Amino acid sequence: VMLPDGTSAYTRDGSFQVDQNGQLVTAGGFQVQPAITIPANALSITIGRDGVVSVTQQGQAAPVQVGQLNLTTFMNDTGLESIGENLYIETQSSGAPNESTPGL
Amino acid sequence: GATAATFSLSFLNSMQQNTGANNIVATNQNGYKPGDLVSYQINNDGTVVGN
Amino acid sequence: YSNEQEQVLGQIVLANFANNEGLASQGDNVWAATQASGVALLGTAGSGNF
Amino acid sequence: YSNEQEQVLGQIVLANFANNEGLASQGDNVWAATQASGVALLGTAGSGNFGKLTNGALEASNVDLSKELVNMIVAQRNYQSNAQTIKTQDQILNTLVNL
Amino acid sequence: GKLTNGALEASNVDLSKELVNMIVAQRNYQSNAQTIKTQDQILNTLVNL
Amino acid sequence: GKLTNGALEASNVDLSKELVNMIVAQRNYQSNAQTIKTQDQILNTLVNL
Amino acid sequence: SFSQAVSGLNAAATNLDVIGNNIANSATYGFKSGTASFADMFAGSKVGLGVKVAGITQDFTDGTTTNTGRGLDVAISQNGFFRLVDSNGSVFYSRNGQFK
Amino acid sequence: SFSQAVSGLNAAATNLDVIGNNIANSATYGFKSGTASFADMFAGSKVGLGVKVAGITQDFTDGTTTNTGRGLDVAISQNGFFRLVDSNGSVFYSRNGQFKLDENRNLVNMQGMQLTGYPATGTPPTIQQGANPAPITIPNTLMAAKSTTTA
Amino acid sequence: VKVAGITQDFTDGTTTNTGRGLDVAISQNGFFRLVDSNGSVFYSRNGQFK
Amino acid sequence: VKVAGITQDFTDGTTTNTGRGLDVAISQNGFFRLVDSNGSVFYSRNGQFKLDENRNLVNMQGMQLTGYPATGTPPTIQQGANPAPITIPNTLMAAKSTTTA
């Protein structure tokens, strides 16, 4: 997730909401990377086992992919520093953030 | 204009005895016309068979 | 009416929001638009996303 | 018509899916095509993988009430057993709290 | 269609079909009542917890 | 509307639906009483502490 | 959920009322039987929220033609409807041919 | 702990709701029974966290074909689905055969969705299967005369 | 702990038949748009109108 | 005390008929072999198999049922071949010129 400072925090809570602009944000109002935008006329949101986010529009015969949700892993999970709001940030004891597809 | 079918026709197992009259017992051939999928099933021994 | 003729008097408009949750409930089973919910998109029933 | 002459006005089309169970029920005893159900294959009755139409007749439901009235009993018993487990855990937590 | 004089058209209600449908609908109603009773017992079990 | 002489307008109350609504309202009342009992237990714990 | 059972009970009651009304009109000139048409009401979830009556459909099949011996009763065969007017000029239609 | 029995209770409630829905639709033409599918929820520990409802599966088996005597009741034996269109143009599929001829002369079901099919074009009209399905209509438009060309 | 929010569950409820011609129920998404005496705009799913 | 382990009870359950042609159960011993979308191989006794969009036989969770494929004309079960996901194609089955009568 992207903090207002532009830095990246990491959260495990999955209750996501949509802001007035149509983007996916964490329930604390923080915008979760990658930028996954849900359009105005969305009927149903399908998030697959591998993090592929799709929406189905009215009158459109095929579902439309609006992004790809990835998972970040750390070689040392304990070293992450909590900043509240169910958010962890990376320290030097928490290794480095490794982005990966959910199932890889 | 299609290629004529060349095949081995066999009268094996046939017989000539004092029957009722000259009659054909059976005929078989391994060719078939084009067919589209109609049904599918899973057999008792596990084979998947499409009819 | 009684002259075997009918007269349309209006069409009920429906509102759809970009964030249905951000709505601030005012009670009386009634919601109010909020910056979190965004502006209301107006339309007719049974058409589009309505 | 009245001149002793027939005219065709249209032919009913039938749709078959790769995955019938992937259809989403929209109510009004009506199904909707979805990606899991696959694209609808259109055709005519009595040809390919489409059954014939029976005119002047209606297809009734396949719900067997004897079977359902049995099931319901089994599900009631399972639900009550789960509630018993819930109350057991409640008594456990009460025991630990009372210390 | 033409008009028949000195005659009246009766109703098209067959009593046998109506009686059989009444029996079937009664059975369906009792099945739904059994469902209602099932939900009643479930809710009673939860409240008695 | 039209007036019909020699006839009376009976009530529009159907007993079956009213009985079902009574059952549902009884269940709602019992659940609400359970909530009341739950609140009565939390204040007891705090008062006793 | 109580809603599905309540809707099913209401639909069964409606069907039973329709059947009883048809029975009450077994001997009624110009009467057409009725049948309730049911539809399910799936709404978002897959749990089958309940059932609803989509409407009541008439059965406009000609009944048996019975002679009465009076000249002022007219039976109608095949399609068609007798046209009547009330005291206020409204137009109505009926298959009953008992006139005076 | 609690979540295990909570998931069990939720699964039992879903099963009972599916059964109640099936019963409520005992007499509904074109209805297919539903059944809940359950699966385990193991997560690392061997204690078996809980159960979840994997989905609802329909039983797409043919029901009884009951004679009604109307000419607009048509039943699909074996596989097949009637194709319908609403006012938005969305395509739907249904096994119901209760079609009614509306005021605009189209074949629609009880809820008003228009039955679709291959239209007839030309003189004499014949079904052209190369076209996309269109709503079926039955106009009263008098049929014109054809001067003879072959006797 | 801190209450992160109070989120609603905007799933469609059961459609219960009543028989009043002034009652309207919303299927799928959409809201009824209302105004009070002060001109404030409100949104409600309750369809019991008089 | 120490929890030594969790032992499964691998006894055969009741076989209940459903009437679905894609529904199959195992009596006695044996497990169905499935493959995940990432290629990981699993084993399960559940027999709720359905045809997916791409004409493959998958269970509820989307794992493809695996087995010996068919090759040749006419095709035959290749007992020496590695198990592969089962697919039921709807492709047109061509004609064979007659060879023996």
Image (cartoon, coloured by chain):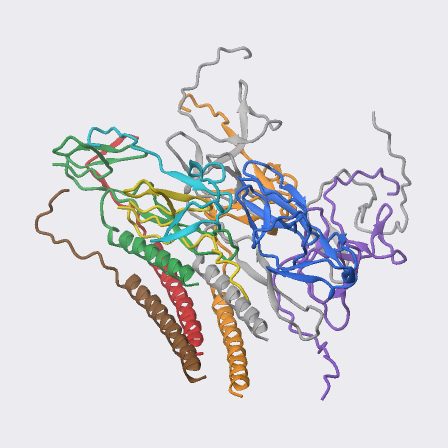
Chain colours: A blue, C cyan, D orange, E red, F brown, G green, I yellow, J purple
Relative to G80, A39 lies left or right: right
Q: Is residue J97 visible?
A: yes
Provide residue J98's location: percent of width, then percent of height. 85, 39
Provide residue E34's location: percent of width, then percent of height. 41, 69
The picture quadrant where one finds residue D45 is top right
Question: Relative to the observer, which residue lies in front, G28 or A18?
Answer: A18
Relative to C7, G69 lies left or right: left
Provide residue F41's location: percent of width, then percent of height. 41, 79
Where the C terminus of chain J falls, by quadrant?
Answer: top right
Question: Relative to the observer, which residue lies in front, D45 or F47?
Answer: F47
Using the image, determine if residue A67 lies above or below residue I14.
above
Using the image, determine if residue G86 lies above or below residue D73.
above
Say which residue appears at 71% left-offset and 44% top-offset: B37
Q: Is residue D35 visible?
A: no
Q: How many marks?
A: 0
Provide residue F26's location: percent of width, then percent of height. 33, 70
The picture quadrant where one finds residue B31 is top right
Where the N terminus of chain J falls, by quadrant?
Answer: bottom right
Name of the residue lying farthest toward the left: F6
Question: Relative to the observer, which residue lies in front, G78 or G66?
Answer: G78
The picture quadrant where one finds residue G67 is top left
Relative to G79, B46 lies left or right: right
Question: Relative to the observer, which residue lies in front, G6 or C29?
Answer: C29
Using the image, determine if residue A64 lies above or below residue A72.
above
